[PDB]
């Protein structure tokens, strides 16, 4: 799958297995002993069994089935909801430690910024991808971590960070709405649909209210527009294009995250905004949308940054905590 | 709805102010020598019915006197329907336009300074408290500065530092249009009032992830019941179109309409609350007015907005509601026309 070459510390002679257990996804970071390979894997949390089965498989294939030489470090919120369930599922384990979620995210991000080349990049449709040589000025920054929800962290110094804000309108909202509305079963089908979509069929644009014309005034604002009469089936029967709905709600959720990230950056006098989590997925349209929102509100005085291992910030911090 | 106010009838021109929004037209007029301000709202979807209302107002309240009627149009829609108004009212004294933001702030400032029992606070703990803004009790410079969060299809946010000193700040495309569009399509709710009834009896916990569901307990600075991901529980042929019918058939009753209505009402309300808070923080404003057609005196919506402002500001900022929230723009237009007929 996804690997980085990095000279890990194997002084403890231990197979370190870091797990970020979110509401919806589990992310693992691990290194076969003496491999000098960081390995990354993502699965869904619902069906907690099918995941615990993943942790067994990693231990079987990558540490010769040796539980006694395996240490699990649990991060995210399942780290508490599931600390005991892990001991119950892995009785011969050498140990299970925890690493607080926000501290995991920042240690992971600081590691990727300072240590790993070709990891930090800008993206817009104009310029395309520019790699930022951060591992070759950095502080202060915001991390906007987009998962089910949105966590926003302020980082002033290497070990000084706080959670300044958040939103319940994250990836979970986008995935949930588009799944229920369109029947799409994969985030990739939602993304492929959004790519060919025209949001103008479901959104009220500035031009639609008045007569920038393509600016959205109201996301999904065009949609709403005893028995004695005909059945109100003309309403129930009104139809909307799946690609158009996907583009509308991708813009709505992405622009909103962008605006909140810009406002928090404004309050905190921060120029550098990192997007983390499992939301952009390297999708050019999502990245362009988040980059443009930061560019638009700041008139280019602030910068959106993306991460090749955006999903693995927490697990990476947790892995490094093992020593 | 009507208010007692000793109007200046000047040359007796009958001033019919219309705020034309995305979905709604909000009308303010005063029959000559009535000393009554009168208020009506109508959808703009059916042009015949909107134009019929204006005709009925002129017939019943100005004795059918078209030649002494002035229509002043405001809202984003003032431009788009100017020609519809010209073709429907060829006999009238005149049609003018008033700028949207000036209309909103002239209207709100009039309500704040002149009309009693207009401005109130609401939360579920304290109930409604009337703020005596027009009295002299809440007088001078406990009024300014303030934010107006004008919620219609979208959200407009205006800052007012002092009389005649106002500007637009960043708003949101996640407004009433978003809530109404999503719930109408997903749930088949027929009216905004049905969506709010369904929301009142709903349980959002069945479609939302709470902090409790993720962290198994309290956590940073959030209770277990706090919402972590709106609709976050829901995601767990080459077809082109979706309809309510297709969503209802495909999903049967896997998710309950009331629970969906409560989830998206909280999601959109909490989001507007946060953006209002963040703009008030940047501009060092304590006073946040909610206007437009969104709250509609709905106790849960008002509790949601007030709690969000109170939570983010740790009590330093306050949400204010308006008995005539829908009419701010139409009221400002009316006051301009009234000064012209003086
Ligand atoms: C980490 C996990 C559990 C996964 C998580 C992830 C995302 C969300 C998103 N939801 C959300 N986030 C916030 N943040 C704030 C900010 N406050 C600052 C002062 O201290 C108190 C909090 C207020 C608020 O209402 N929400 N709602 C919640 C929880």
Image (cartoon, coloured by chain):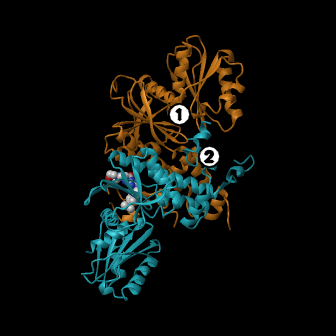
Chain colours: A cyan, B orange
Q: Quadrant of ligand 1?
A: bottom left
Disc 2 crowd rating (10 Å Cα; few below 14, some 14-19, many 20+) is: many
Query: In whole angstroms, how far apart are the C-alphas of marks 1 and 2?
Result: 20 Å
A169 lies above or below A277: above
Q: Foreground: B46 or A64?
A: A64
Q: Foreground: B272 or A145?
A: A145
Q: Is residue A18 left or right of residue A160?
A: right
Residue B94: which quarter of the image? top right
Q: Residue at x 72, y 21 (%)?
A: B90
Q: Residue at x 36, y 37 (%)?
A: B283
Do marks 1 and 2 share a chain? no
Q: SS at mark 2?
A: loop
Q: Are marks 1 and 2 in contact (CB under 8 Å)?
A: no
Q: SS at mark 1?
A: helix
Q: Foreground: A69 or A155?
A: A155
Foreground: disc 1 or disc 2? 2
Q: Would you say the beta carbon of the disc 1 residue lies within 8 angstroms of ligand 1?
A: no
Kindly identify which numbered label has been placed on residue A222. Answer: 2
Regarding residue B272, the answer to whether it shows in the image is no
Kindly identify which numbered label has been placed on residue A183. Answer: none
Location of residue A302 in the rendering, given as x and y in whole percent from the top left corner: 39, 49
Kindly identify which numbered label has been placed on residue B326. Answer: 1
Location of residue A294 in the rendering, given as x and y in whole percent from the top left corner: 44, 49
Q: Residue at x 58, y 35 (%)?
A: B21
Please count the marks in the image.
2
Location of residue B25 in the rendering, given as x and y in whole percent from the top left corner: 60, 33
What chain does badge 2 belong to?
A: A
Regarding residue B233, the answer to whether it shows in the image is yes
Residue at the top extreme, as displayed: B11
A236 lies above or below B127: below
């Amino acid at each position: 799958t996804q690997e980085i070459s990095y000279n890990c510390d194997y002084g403890d002679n231990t197979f370190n297995l870091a797990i970020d257990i979110g509401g919806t996804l589990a992310k693992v970071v691990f290194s076969p002993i003496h491999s000098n390979r960081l390995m990354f894997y993502t699965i869904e949390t619902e069906k907690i069994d099918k995941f615990m089965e993943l942790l067994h498989s990693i231990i079987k294939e990558h540490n010769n089935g040796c539980y006694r030489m395996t240490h699990i470090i649990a991060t995210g919120g399942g780290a508490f909801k599931f600390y005991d369930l892990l001991y119950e599922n892995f009785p011969q384990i050498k140990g299970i430690s925890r690493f607080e979620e926000m501290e995991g995210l920042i240690h992971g991000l600081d590691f990727f910024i300072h240590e790993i080349p070709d990891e930090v990049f800008t993206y817009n449709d104009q310029d395309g991808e520019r790699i930022i040589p951060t591992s070759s000025a950095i502080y202060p920054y915001l991390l906007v971590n987009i998962g089910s929800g949105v966590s926003i962290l302020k980082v002033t110094e290497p070990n000084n960070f706080s959670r300044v804000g958040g939103s319940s309108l994250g990836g979970g909202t986008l995935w949930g709405l588009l799944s229920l509305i369109t029947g799409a079963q994969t985030y990739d089908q939602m993304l492929d649909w959004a790519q060919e979509g025209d949001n103008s069929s479901v959104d009220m644009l500035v031009g639609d209210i008045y007569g920038k014309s393509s600016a959205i005034a109201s996301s999904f604002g065009k949609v709403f527009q005893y028995s004695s009469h005909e059945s109100i089936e003309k309403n129930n029967g009104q139809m909307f294009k799946n690609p158009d709905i996907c583009k509308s709600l991708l813009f709505a959720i992405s622009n909103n995250i962008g605006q909140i990230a810009y406002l928090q950056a404004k309050i905190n006098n921060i120029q550098n905004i990192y997007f983390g989590g499992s939301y952009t997925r390297g999708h050019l349209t999502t990245m362009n949308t988040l980059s443009y929102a930061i560019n638009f509100w700041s008139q280019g005085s602030k910068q959106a940054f993306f991460l090749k291992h955006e999903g693995y910030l927490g697990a990476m911090g947790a892995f490094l905590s093992a020593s």
